């Protein structure tokens, strides 16, 4: 039950108590993911209009 | 002094952000017009509150915050609310139509067309920072914007601010305050693409906030205002160290250092007490030992789970009010001899304690009663994995039938991103079991 | 209309409970994976406790205490008694036991030999028994070499404890036995002892000079009915009930089952369960737990009661399935889910 | 400003649509001339969802009236609120559709569809942000069925990413104008499977039985059937017309009600339904017991024959929201054998403080039930009873159609039935 690193100031204090010791994707790669999903949307919509055109 | 920029995404983040900045102002003595009489340095200063508030020559104290929603209704409240004068227009960003609770819609379809805008507005706040620490991102798991757009924003922040820290306050989905059936999908999609981009995440289960409001506040049908006023008390306790003089958790880095020895396991459990109903004429003021003991009761945890059946990796006690170190260690001693507190063998069995003499501020007319002392315990327990298990199980039930999956595929998402996200959660639950179970 | 699920088809006990529940016309059974339920008769292994108590407007009750395995595991119980100050290492009603991991894997090997050498030098009886939870696989021996070598040949943790060389023998027969007591703990953590116990007796005369033939040393109902040739001779199914056993203690020993044995049993049950209450209690939990336990005791020639093991999924004596199972619906289920005596249990009052 | 464009087509479409605007115009304080005269701001909060604002604080519905004959629309223009509809939004021909799906879809209808789409485009261009469209029509006639579905196909081509919603009256031999209604309905139901996000199935038989048995109406009339449709339409749209966060925005509703793209045909329900003991107060339990009762459901399907994929309930009036949750969570927890267990929390509830005219409180039921297949089964059987003999086909082959197109519509609906069947097990 040890207290360590006691720091006190005008608005409070902070300390530590030890009971027992122990025993990314680049900007380019994000635009590609975004544009890839935008392309599949454009493809899916293209098949819808082709369906409607028929 | 190093600055912290807050980012609120979606309806949950924006309404929760509102409650926090209302509370922050009452705490630092900032009036709705932005004026702060106590600040004797007009239009400048590197005080502790300057980490969250910038200043103008006119003496206005402006939050370092950005509000982002794909629909204008929620953010319009801020523009005409009590604290409309705190922010300037650039800080509030709104779209025309929302993500319809569709992760793929917020991350891809709509997100792609507004992502760089949030970044530009953020850059503007960063340009006022002489030493930016990082970001605090508030969002929900279940919303289309909260889930979808947030994960895209985190990916870009890691690119545009590599060395900066990023913390989350995330709303875990709760059927009692939700009408969306697909929130499990969204929650798991956003956790998979955000995991490697967040250094510390404080999950708040709406189920827990809901029950605390009914049990302790005697609210029969808690509203969002009730849920947010209480969530901002917990958030205030967690961010207080960054806004007040102190030596514990003085920068966002210290949160990872003191609470996250393993990077993927960065979801500390929060526990707050006391929550007292203001309608009570007068309440027997609780002691340091009693409120500390309450930190180990499931009834006031931000996520309902049983820490008795997990292993702690870290533990911070954040006291506010009439509390001296002598009382703290006395209660801790007793709690150890009665409570089941099992730490991981590769982490010390100890507690970092922070005391702020200013007791919790209560919003006038709010639901919480003024108390002489309160505490928030931040403990990284393997028990919080119970929340991942519940959510992953709901995901499996629907995904096994591919129910609702066509909505996500139709917005440009590939079906394989579902199982890719799910296998990552399977790996997250395994990490918790390897660390906690024998 | 209450609802419940069944996730352990192999439970003869709760099979009857589910049979009685449906007979009440006020309980409806649901599929094993339907989350909207009031009562879960859960599986034995890996019961998903973390998914309980998260259904809006449903008080959920499960038939297993999370964490009670610490008491119902051979090695776990030994660790619990030696490390729990409430039980202490000097516990007088639990045989001197040690945890021994096979050498192919803390461990108490050297600690076991130390006490073993002490007995060998002191002319004292030095007969130990090795067993584990992965058995039907038990070995009784007086040589430490055989005991340790037997465990190394296996691959699971084992426990070596003192073999009771002076067990109380029934007459006529000169035969060993054990006592099974069923204990039901409810959501409020009341400890109820079933007024009906059973003696699982050996139909073979106890022989202290041959631990090789384990038919007269192991009173398991399956061993007696398989390797014992006098099965059912003295009592039906090698099962004596409290009424008979009590009359015997009076005629033979001039005492009662209550004074000589039952007080110690009730004290042991209290001590064991009260010890772990802070760890498994569901008093302030988002769901509620109850569980049925099967304690097994030994009695020596001095009428001292020794605890053998605790069973988490115990079976019942055929003659007592109806009385007990209904008793489970009364104090465990209907106590939280009431329906629109002279209790068959004995309340063991204690300080929570 | 999430505006919705309303379209009503044909005799049935325009008569039901009229009563609808009559009902909600009252709930929002709009009088027959478009002048607001309410007493609550909640009336005008989301007024722009269905109404345009004109000069002099005038509110003009965003509705387009379509028919191939003048008769019905002439009545609307002389009806109670006829003066509130934009004059230019009346688009109509003179030939008629002769209850012929082919005439509405390929010949007569085709000659008039472009002019209708000119008005849609005009109303859309004025929308700050268009949520989508809602169409009212029957499936058993010619205009609302044949041309109605022709309009959806074209509206979807020009607005591919907007929500398409319909209130579709389904024909029944018990309430029938002509024997070819099953032909027209089977042709439309395939259009809807492809081109609508949400379709509220409204069986005229259920409406009739409700009027005869429950409402105790000796001789029902279309007017009586339309009172039920008016109230139901007002109920299911309450989420949209008032301040709320549940089911608001057509796409969010579709995202939480449609687990599979083709299984988007809903069963509506309303409570109360009292016969003139009409002043008695109705308790929350009663509202819930009835709203879920089959005799209050307007699809003519027994829910206990299938399973609910999702359910959306709307309670209106000043009541105990705590008590609402309790009774809803009681129906579910008392009949969970009828809710699919692979969609957690598939029953959602919303409360609204403004009640319908003359009711302390009411409840509207919106269920995506697999029991709806019973409805498509009826139509399918009635269809094949005639088509196997090619009876009455000459009306359609004479307008340019081929028998092959009938065989396909047949197979397309029998497929839709098998789809509902596999998700019921
Ligand atoms: N605690 C709390 N939870 C909220 C609040 N607002 C919404 N939620 C929760 O957030 C989830 C829904 O996500 P939203 O935040 O509304 O969605 P969004 O981020 O606005 O994205 P959209 O789908 O485009 O609307 C549900 O689980 C709600 O319970 C709030 O103000 N406080
Ligand atoms: N230390 C000891 N002294 C004397 N007998 C012992 C003993 N340990 C075990 N036994 C004998 O072994 C039997 C019980 O074995 P144990 O309970 O450990 O195995 P098990 O769990 O597979 C049987 P059950 O669980 O049904 O009681 C008893 O009949 C008892 O006579
Ligand atoms: N509920 C209801 N159904 C109607 C009404 N008028 C016609 N119907 C039904 O609609 C079908 C006839 O379609 P109708 O609208 O008259 O054809 P259209 O004018 O060419 O589109 C028949 O099944 C009628 O039962 C009405 O006012 N209300
Ligand atoms: Ca200053
Ligand atoms: Ca990073
Ligand atoms: Ca012509
Ligand atoms: Mg939103
Ligand atoms: Mg056993
Ligand atoms: Mg007609």
Image (spheres, coloured by chain):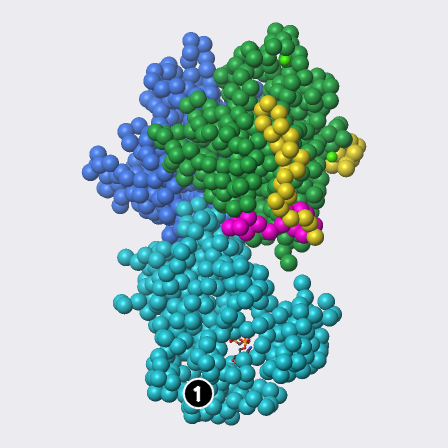
Dot 1: chain letter? C
Whether residue B347 is in magenta: the answer is yes
Name the image quarter holding residue B115: top right
State which region is magenta: B335-350
Q: Which chain is blue?
A: D
Q: Which chain is green?
A: B
Q: Which residue is mark 1?
A: C170
Q: Colour of chain C?
A: cyan
Q: Please state the horizontal and vertical placement of residue C94, each as a whole percent of the image.
A: 52, 71
Q: Please state the horizontal and vertical placement of residue A14, each as a whole percent of the image.
A: 62, 32
User: Looking at the image, which is closer to me, D142 or B397?
Assistant: B397
Check the image and name the residue furthest to the top.
B58
Q: Please state the horizontal and vertical placement of residue B144, each as a whole percent of the image.
A: 59, 34
Local crowd size for mark 1, using a 10 Å CA cut-off: few (<14), some (14–19), many (≥20)? some
Residue D406 as seen in the image, left or right of residue C62: right
Rendered residue at 63%/50% (across/down): B343
Q: Please state the horizontal and vertical placement of residue C242, each as a whole percent of the image.
A: 37, 79
Q: Which chain is yellow?
A: A
Count the marks: how many? 1
Q: Is residue D279 above or below residue B386?
A: above
Rendered residue at 60%/82% (across/down): C124
Q: Is residue C347 above or below residue A13?
A: below
Rendered residue at 70%/33% (across/down): B253
Q: Is residue A18 above or below residue C112?
A: above
Rendered residue at 56%/28% (across/down): B356
Name the image quarter holding residue C193: bottom left
The secondary structure making up most of the magenta span is loop
Residue D202 as seen in the image, left or right of residue B358: left
């Amino acid at each position: 039950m040890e207290v360590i690193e006691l720091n006190k100031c005008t608005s409070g204090q902070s300390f530590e108590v030890i009971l027992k010791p122990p025993s990314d994707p680049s900007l380019e790669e994000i635009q590609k993911k975004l544009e890839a999903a935008e392309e599949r949307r454009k493809y899916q919509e293209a098949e819808l209009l082709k369906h409607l055109a028929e | 002094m190093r600055e912290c920029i807050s980012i609120h995404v979606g309806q949950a983040g924006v309404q929760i952000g509102n409650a926090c900045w209302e509370l922050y102002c009452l705490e630092h003595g900032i009036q709705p017009d932005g004026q702060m009489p106590s600040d004797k340095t007009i239009g400048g200063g590197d005080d502790s509150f300057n980490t969250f508030f910038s200043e103008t020559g006119a003496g206005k104290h402006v939050p370092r915050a950005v509000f982002v929603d794909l629909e204008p209704t929620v953010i319009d409240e801020v523009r005409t609310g009590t604290y409309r004068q705190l922010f300037h227009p650039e800080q509030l960003i709104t779209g025309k139509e929302d993500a319809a609770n569709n992760y793929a819609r917020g991350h891809y379809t709509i997100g792609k067309e507004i992502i760089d805008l949030v970044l530009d507005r953020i850059r503007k706040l960063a340009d006022q920072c002489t030493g930016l620490q990082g970001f605090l991102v508030f969002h929900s798991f279940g919303g289309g914007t909260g889930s979808g757009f947030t994960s895209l924003l985190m990916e870009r922040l890691s690119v545009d601010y590599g060395k900066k820290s990023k913390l989350e306050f995330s709303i875990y989905p709760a059927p009692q305050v939700s009408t969306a059936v697909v929130e499990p999908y969204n929650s798991i999609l956003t956790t998979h693409t955000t995991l490697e981009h967040s250094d510390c995440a404080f999950m708040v289960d709406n189920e827990a906030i809901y029950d605390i409001c009914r049990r302790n506040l005697d609210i029969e049908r808690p509203t969002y205002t009730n849920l947010n006023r209480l969530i901002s008390q917990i958030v205030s306790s967690i961010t207080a160290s960054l806004r007040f003089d102190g030596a514990l958790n003085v920068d966002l880095t210290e949160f990872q250092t003191n609470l996250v020895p393993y990077p993927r396991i960065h979801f500390p459990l929060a526990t707050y007490a006391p929550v007292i109903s203001a309608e009570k004429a007068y309440h027997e003021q609780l002691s340091v030992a009693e409120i500390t003991n309450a930190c180990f009761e499931p009834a006031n945890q931000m996520v309902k789970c049983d820490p008795r059946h997990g292993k702690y990796m870290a533990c911070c006690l954040l006291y506010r009010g009439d509390v001296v170190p002598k009382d703290v260690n006395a209660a801790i001693a007793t709690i150890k001899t009665k409570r089941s507190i099992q730490f991981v063998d590769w982490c010390p069995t100890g507690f970092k304690v922070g005391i702020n003499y200013q007791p919790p501020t209560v919003v006038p007319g709010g639901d919480l009663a003024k108390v002489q002392r309160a505490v928030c315990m931040l403990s990284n327990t393997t028990a919080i994995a119970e929340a991942w298990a519940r959510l992953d199980h709901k995901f499996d039930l629907m995904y096994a039938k591919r129910a609702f999956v066509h909505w996500y595929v139709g917005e440009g998402m590939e079906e394989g991103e579902f199982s890719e996200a799910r296998e990552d959660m399977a790996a997250l639950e395994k990490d918790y079991e390897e660390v906690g179970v024998d | 209309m209450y609802t419940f699920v069944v996730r352990d088809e192999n439970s003869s006990v709760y099979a009857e409970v589910s049979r009685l529940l449906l007979a009440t016309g006020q309980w409806k059974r649901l599929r094993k994976d339907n989350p909207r339920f009031n009562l879960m008769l859960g599986e034995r292994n890996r019961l998903p406790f973390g998914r309980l108590g998260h259904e809006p407007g449903l008080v959920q009750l499960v038939n297993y205490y999370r964490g009670a395995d610490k008491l119902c595991r051979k090695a776990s119980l030994v660790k619990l008694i030696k490390t729990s100050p409430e039980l202490s290492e000097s516990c007088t009603w639990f045989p001197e036991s040690y945890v021994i991991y096979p050498t192919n894997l803390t461990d108490e090997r050297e600690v076991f030999l130390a006490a073993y050498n002490r007995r060998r030098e002191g002319r004292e009886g030095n007969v130990w028994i090795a067993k584990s939870s992965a058995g039907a696989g038990i070995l009784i021996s007086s040589e430490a070499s055989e005991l340790l070598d037997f465990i190394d040949e296996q691959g699971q943790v084992h426990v070596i404890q003192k073999y009771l060389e002076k067990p109380l023998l029934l007459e006529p027969g000169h035969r060993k036995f054990d006592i099974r007591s069923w204990v039901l703990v409810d959501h409020l953590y009341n400890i109820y002892l079933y007024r009906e116990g059973v003696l699982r007796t050996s139909s073979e005369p106890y022989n202290s000079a041959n631990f090789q033939d384990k038919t007269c040393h192991l009173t398991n109902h399956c061993i007696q009915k398989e390797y014992s040739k006098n099965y059912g001779r003295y009592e039906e199914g090698n099962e004596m009930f409290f009424e008979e056993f009590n009359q015997y203690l009076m005629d033979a020993l001039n005492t009662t089952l209550e004074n000589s044995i039952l007080l110690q049993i009730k004290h042991i049950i209290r001590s064991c369960l009260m010890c772990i209450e802070p760890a498994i209690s569901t008093k302030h939990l988002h769901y509620q737990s109850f569980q049925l336990f099967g304690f097994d005791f030994m009695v020596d020639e001095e009428l001292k009661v020794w605890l053998i093991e605790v069973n988490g999924a115990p079976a019942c004596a055929q003659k007592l399935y109806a009385e007990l199972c209904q008793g489970i619906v009364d104090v465990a289920i209907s106590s939280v889910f009431p329906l629109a005596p002279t209790s068959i249990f004995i309340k063991l009052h204690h300080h929570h | 400003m999430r505006e919705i464009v309303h379209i009503q087509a044909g005799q049935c479409g325009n008569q039901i649509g009229a009563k609808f605007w009559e009902v909600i115009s009252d709930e929002h304080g709009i009088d027959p001339t478009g002048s607001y005269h309410g007493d609550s701001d909640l009336q005008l909060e989301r007024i722009n969802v269905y109404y345009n604002e004109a000069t002099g604080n005038k509110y003009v519905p965003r509705a387009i009236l379509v028919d191939l004959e003048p008769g019905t629309m002439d009545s609307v223009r002389s009806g109670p609120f006829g003066q509130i509809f934009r004059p230019d939004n009346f688009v109509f021909g003179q030939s008629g559709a002769g209850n012929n799906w082919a005439k509405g879809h390929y010949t007569e209808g085709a000659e008039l569809v472009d002019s209708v789409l000119d008005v849609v485009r005009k109303e859309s261009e004025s929308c700050d942000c268009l949520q989508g469209f809602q169409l009212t029509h029957s499936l058993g006639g010619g205009t609302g069925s044949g041309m109605g579905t022709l309009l959806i196909s074209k509206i979807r081509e020009e607005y591919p990413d907007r929500i398409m919603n319909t209130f579709s009256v389904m024909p029944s031999p018990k309430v029938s104008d002509t024997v070819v209604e099953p032909y027209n309905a089977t042709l439309s139901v395939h259009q809807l499977v492809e081109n609508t996000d949400e379709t509220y199935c409204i069986d005229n038989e259920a409406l009739y039985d409700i009027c005869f048995r429950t409402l105790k109406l000796t001789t029902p009339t279309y007017g009586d059937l339309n009172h039920l449709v008016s109230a139901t339409m007002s109920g299911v749209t309450t989420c949209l017309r008032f301040p709320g966060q549940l089911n608001a925005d057509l796409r969010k509703l579709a995202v939480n009600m449609v687990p599979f793209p083709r299984l988007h045909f809903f069963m509506p329900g309303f409570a109360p339904l009292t016969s003139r003991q009409q002043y008695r107060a109705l308790t929350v339990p009663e509202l819930t017991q009835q709203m879920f009762d089959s005799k209050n459901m307007m699809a003519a399907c027994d829910p206990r024959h299938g399973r609910y994929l999702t359910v959306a309930a709307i309670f209106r009036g000043r009541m105990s929201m705590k008590e609402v949750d309790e009774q809803m969570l009681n129906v579910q927890n008392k009949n969970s054998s009828y809710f699919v267990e692979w969609i957690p929390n598939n029953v959602k509830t919303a409360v609204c403080d403004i009640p319908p005219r003359g009711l302390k409180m009411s409840a509207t039921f919106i269920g995506n039930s697999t029991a709806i297949q019973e409805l498509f089964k009826r139509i399918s059987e009635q269809f094949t009873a005639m088509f196997r003999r090619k009876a009455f086909l000459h009306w359609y082959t004479g307008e340019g159609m081929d028998e092959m197109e009938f065989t396909e519509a047949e197979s397309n609906m029998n497929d839709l039935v098998s789809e509902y069947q596999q998700y019921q097990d």
